[PDB]
Amino acid sequence: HMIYAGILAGPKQFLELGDRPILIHTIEKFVLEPSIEKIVVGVHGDWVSHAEDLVDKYLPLYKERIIITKGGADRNTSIKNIIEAIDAYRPLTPEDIVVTHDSVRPFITLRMIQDNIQLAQNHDAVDTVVEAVDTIVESTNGQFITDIPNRAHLYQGQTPQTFRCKDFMDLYGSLSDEEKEILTDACKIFVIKGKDVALAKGEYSNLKITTVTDLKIAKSMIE
Amino acid sequence: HMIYAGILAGPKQFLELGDRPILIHTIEKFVLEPSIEKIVVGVHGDWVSHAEDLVDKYLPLYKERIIITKGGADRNTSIKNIIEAIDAYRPLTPEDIVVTHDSVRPFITLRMIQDNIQLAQNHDAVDTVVEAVDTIVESTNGQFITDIPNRAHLYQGQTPQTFRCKDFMDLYGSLSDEEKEILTDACKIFVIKGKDVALAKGEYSNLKITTVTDLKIAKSMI
Ligand SMILES: [Ca+2]
Ligand SMILES: [Ca+2]
């Protein structure tokens, strides 16, 4: 079967970290992995040719390994779009897998990618997580605490999130627009459909670069 | 009724941020609120005179407003010690409140302190909080996901945690040693005892300085 990387890049990913755009750092981490067929990057339609320029400029040796495609309005629409681009490259079979990952998580390691791929063999999906270190409070109303979850069972969700392309299409396709609005996480869709989602070990350093503070942390990390 | 600040300081709080220790930064924000009767600081037994010298050196003008006392083995014992220090200073009424706050959260704002005091009026306790940024995943088994709760209902706990001194003492005194181990922060005690704890709005800039990089970030903010 095939294994693809699905890079969600639909913004800080076009910003330089060190001497290369964040997006490039992230794609770089996937190019060495021998078991990856293509690296499929979902970008906002207006930034597709820009993303292609970056590949030409920063990763010319890996041009043919990388497919830039139009992402969607939310992450799951981008995943679907990625899977469609994959299907257009080589018609999907039930066993073909996509390793989905945030563009702004440049500190992913081969160990994480490899664990995700390995876990996907015997499970429906894989979610990369770390132990939650934040104290988490629940409030449905946003006015008072409706409860405090048992912290012993809480994890901070990261990416990759890994699953069979066909499996994601089938489950996502079964959702109403209203359900898609609520079930914004790909693993959540598998979980609520009663599927087996294994935990993969993330890393505290697997930072998501969202805010200008995250950017500062990222810069300090590359030394 | 009196309003007190209860600063939990026991180790980054004694490290310099700009030109002053972080602890002094944190104390200063509470001095900005005129309605605070005393700022009570719980530190490690051996660090009391050190913290006193810090107050003398950096806030001599405000030293009368600050009490340094010996904190405890966990944050809840330190809160207990703080409240006993308050009671030693001025006998408690059932309505005196304590605004408890991490020493290593020096970017607390006046607004946050004010909201905590206001919200404590009509509630059992107050938890200062921000909307959760990460997707939280639950696994009761450590192997597969048992739930991914809706992130829109989830909040990252910060401090201040504010409540009436007597109320804390009453609830805390009713716990066994094992409960006290699981009920690790004040608001958790309140919630499990079926009390009403209001959310106060925190800030994403209300950084808890735990790690070396937190300190680096704090420095860049100042
Ligand atoms: Ca097809
Ligand atoms: Ca609607």
Image: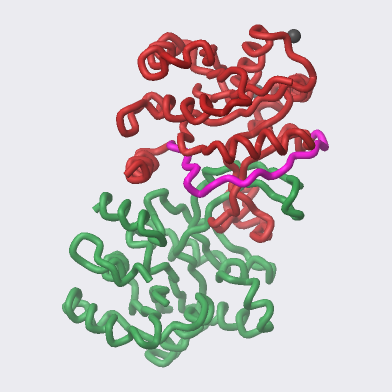
Chain colours: A red, B green
Residue at 47%, 46% (x, y): give it: A205
Q: Quadrant of the N terminus of chain B?
A: bottom left
The foreground one among B27 and B197 is B27
Residue shown at 38% from the left, 71% from the top: B11
A211 over B104 or under it: above or below: above
Is residue A199 in the magenta section?
yes
Residue A77 position by quadrant: top right
Q: Between A133 and A176, which is closer to the camera in this rendering?
A: A133
The residue closer to the viewer here, B108 or B209, is: B209
Q: Give the x, y percent position of residue A57.
A: 36, 15
Residue at the (22%, 83%) spot, across then down: B53
Is residue B154 shown left or right of residue B8? right
Any magenta on residue A126? no
Q: Residue B192 at what x, y percent from top left?
A: 68, 68
Observer-nearest of A39 and A124: A39
Task: Indicate whether A62 appears above or below B86.
Answer: above
Question: Residue A161: x, y in percent?
Answer: 64, 34
Up-down: is B203 above or below A86? below
- Looking at this view, name the residue that lies furthest to the front: A34
- Coordinates of residue B37 in the picture (x, y in percent): 34, 78
Q: Main secondary structure of the magenta part?
A: loop
Residue span colored magenta: A193-209
On screen, B5 above or below A102?
below
Q: Residue furthest bottom?
A: B88
Q: Is residue A176 among what the camera can see?
A: no
